[PDB]
Image 1: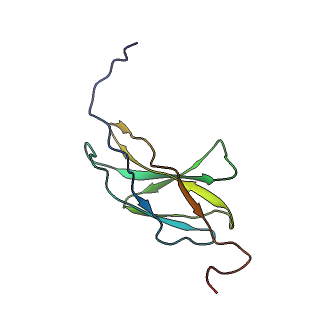
Image 2: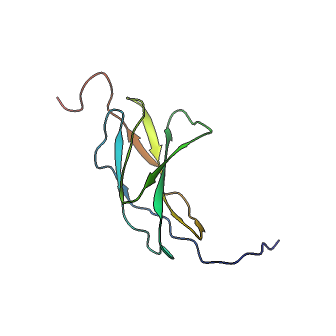
Length: 111
């Protein structure tokens, strides 16, 4: 009905994300600052999981800057990345479902 609480408003939700370099097992990301942070942002948490294989336990990545690189993935496998801003006050929502595919093992990226 009515939950009682006190504090500051939650930060905005980053809706801008770009891929800097997509490695075979590692992938990089690039997003911008949230319209309204509503305070100081400690770090951005990214969520990456097997696009095809949805695992209950998703892996998170702590990033201090607008740049990050997720390592420890499988080649030739799509991964859904999701960057979000976290603030002492609370937590915001996850960015849009970003689809990215790593470099297939068959061979290199270019040829």
